[PDB]
Image (tube, coloured by chain):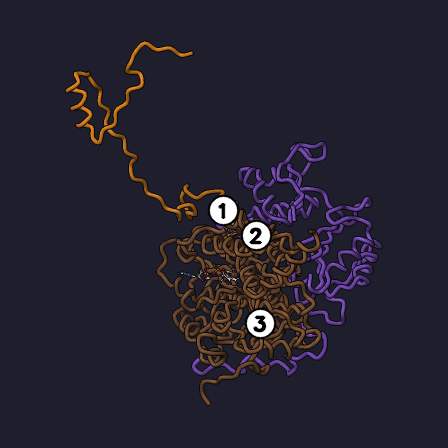
Amino acid sequence: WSSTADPLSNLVLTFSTKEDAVAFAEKNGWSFDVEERKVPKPKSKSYGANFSWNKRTRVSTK
Amino acid sequence: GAGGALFVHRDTPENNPDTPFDFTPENYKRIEAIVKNYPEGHKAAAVLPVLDLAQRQNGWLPISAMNKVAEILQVPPMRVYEVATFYTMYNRKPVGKYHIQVCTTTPCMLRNSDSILEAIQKKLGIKVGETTPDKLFTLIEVECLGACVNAPMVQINDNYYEDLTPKDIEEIIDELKAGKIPKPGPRSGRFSCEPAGGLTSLTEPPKGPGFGVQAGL
Amino acid sequence: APKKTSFGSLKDEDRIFTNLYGRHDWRLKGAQSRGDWYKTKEILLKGPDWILGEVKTSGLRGRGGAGFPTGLKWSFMNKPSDGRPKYLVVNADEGEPGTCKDREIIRHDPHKLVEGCLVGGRAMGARAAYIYIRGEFYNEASNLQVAIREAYEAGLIGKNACGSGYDFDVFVVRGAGAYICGEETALIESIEGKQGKPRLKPPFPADVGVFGCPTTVANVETVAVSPTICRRGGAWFASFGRERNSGTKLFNISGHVNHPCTVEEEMSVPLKELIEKHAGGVIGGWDNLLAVIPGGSSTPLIPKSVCETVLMDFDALVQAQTGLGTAAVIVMDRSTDIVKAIARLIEFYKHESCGQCTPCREGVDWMNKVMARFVKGDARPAEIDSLWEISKQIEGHTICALGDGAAWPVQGLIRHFRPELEERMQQFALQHQ
Ligand SMILES: NC(=O)C1=CN([C@@H]2O[C@H](COP(=O)(O)OP(=O)(O)OC[C@H]3O[C@@H](n4cnc5c(N)ncnc54)[C@H](O)[C@@H]3O)[C@@H](O)[C@H]2O)C=CC1
Ligand SMILES: Cc1cc2nc3c(=O)[nH]c(=O)nc-3n(C[C@H](O)[C@H](O)[C@H](O)COP(=O)(O)O)c2cc1C
Ligand code: SF4
Ligand code: FES
């Protein structure tokens, strides 16, 4: 079986904002690394572009 | 019901990429004329006719013919395979000299297309979807062929034979296997889509160019 | 007496397709003899707006089967050019069971179709016309090509069509056995060398169509009646039929009739009068009638009680919950197994589905299996309601209207012949313990 010796291997905490997590870590004395949230950028979708008269976006199959 | 024909190609001694196929020079001229009917930036539109031409030259479509069509038109082979498997008139397997197609949809079914199917089966001694040992005749069931007024009907090698009785189809088969060309169309003294007797419409002579043209024109 | 109320008897002088039965020369000489290609130069020089106005005031609706107003649809293409060429696509696929009219139009007077192509292209400002003919109509396509060749040598089409200074081409493209390729977007996709799979709307063909260019897809009957409408006026065409149901129509009467045939008749003619006058009556007498499918396989069937007074136009058949469709009348007498007929239609739709979208691809096959079991009687009565719900889950949820055309016949059969299905299930249960 898989054996461990550290008691915090399963500890995961949930927070509403980054600032809340930072405050909790600071008041508990833990040094932390923060990663900014990654949000997918808005994209421009066009179903008509599948059948362009002169562009490369025209699809060869459906 | 079930289609019965697979849509996966497995290489075979008589159907493989090295099977010989090539267009004739006359067919190449016809292909050139076909491609000249579409805008210069869209040559894939010629896939449907050219593929058909290959079959008209070969009788069926080996994978070599599809590869040749794809190479000629600069289209990827998978697109040609897609077209060849989507459309039911393409033969991805050899067929007899005469391809017999019997419409069995409801308008033709109401006028006893089953008798025509049974007469063909009895005359040729083969099941639907089977090809005779001689190989001249191949039989299949098709959907509505657009001649429901003249029912029951049959299509043999892009020829329409209409208003069929079992005797009519027996004579058609007899003169087809005797090397003769049967007369296409109805077989009831009708020869068109008019009523069988009387000609209830269009009896008065048609009128000339300027019969009822409006003023100021 | 204005506002006629009884329709169904028009003489030959008011008929458009005067060579419907092929008793006169279909070549150019015969067409000119019958009034074709007459004063087309003046009509072309009247401008696209005049032609669109004549088509609008005519009240002509789409003869393909949907009945969309033709003038508005054609004027959707009356925009200024943006660089892309403009095209007219004529629909000649003719896949609906029971329908045979366009075949006769193409083979017996293709010059009407060619002149209609020219007039419609001028009205829409189209560079060329593409005619998508059914692949099984080889001889009809060859006749159309011969007529196009005669028109090209006569100067009626091509460079400087007639003397109008308008350049216009006509091309013939043949399909390869696909009913779904009759749908306008699937037809466009098949022209471009792809599988006959419909594309979603919007965009509509007037914005992005064949080769990504503005195009209009029109039925061959709609295109072919247009030059006559232009020559005789929209008022003459609108004098026939009820309001919003103007003009004449081709009817294909098939099934259990003494003389199955194709005729031209005024729109709002009653169904019984048409059947007993042009088709020789129902086999065995009118009292032998069981059911009628009035507008091709996609329309719901109606029992004999409804066919006594129903009229053959869009509105009256909509009020009868059946629709007009392609005006292809299929007659089933009292010796007909109605369940077997509807199951055969569902099998046709299962074999014609393109498979693109989930509801059609799965549900049509599901209903085919259910109806096959219904024919024998294996099912239980509750399944009937289930079947109804299944059809409701297909209709209005698919890319194209093929799903609707498969769902509607079972809805009609359940609506009008539920006791037949129930008694079939009863007999199957009683026979097999
Ligand atoms: N002639 C034949 O062989 C067959 C005919 N049909 C008939 O086809 C009918 C259904 O076909 P659909 O095309 O799906 O009907 P639809 O109502 O969706 O479209 C009919 C025409 O009207 C145009 N249109 C409709 N709304 C428009 C809008 N808001 N903007 C621009 N254009 C618009 C469309 O471009 C189309 O060309 C059925 O009623 C059926 O009877 C079906 C199978 C075969
Ligand atoms: C599955 C399906 C098949 C169709 N097949 C045809 C056809 O074969 N011929 C036709 O004219 N219309 C057919 N239609 C209807 C087309 O949409 C119609 O031709 C097109 O809208 C032309 O409009 P119009 O009637 O105003 O000329 C079909 C529609 C569907 C959903
Ligand atoms: S409804 Fe049927 S034919 Fe139409 S797009 Fe969907 S799967 Fe294809
Ligand atoms: S039903 Fe047989 S040709 Fe249409």
Q: Mark 3 points at which residue?
A: C250
Chain corresponding to purple in the figure = B
* Chain of the residue displaying label 1: C
Q: Are dots 1 and 3 on a single chain?
A: yes
Secondary structure under badge 2? helix
Query: For the point 28% across and 15% down, which residue is it?
Result: A8
Q: Residue B111 occupies which quadrant of the picture?
A: bottom right
Q: Name the residue under label 2.
A: C367
Q: Residue B18 occupies which quadrant of the picture?
A: top right
Of circles 1 and 2, which is in front? 2
Of circles 3 and 2, which is in front? 2
Chain corresponding to orange in the figure = A
Instruction: Name the N-terminal-most of marks 3 and 2.
Output: 3
Can you tell me whether the CB of the residue at mark 1 lies under 8 Å from the nearest atom of ligand 3?
yes
Query: Which amino acid type is shown beneath numbered disc 3?
Result: Leu
Q: Are dots 1 and 2 on a single chain?
A: yes
Secondary structure under badge 1? helix
Q: How crowded is mark 1: few (under 14 residues within 10 Å), some or many (20 or more)?
A: few
Query: Which amino acid type is shown beneath numbered disc 1?
Result: Thr
Of circles 1 and 3, which is in front? 1
Given residues A56 and B151, the one toward you in this image is: B151
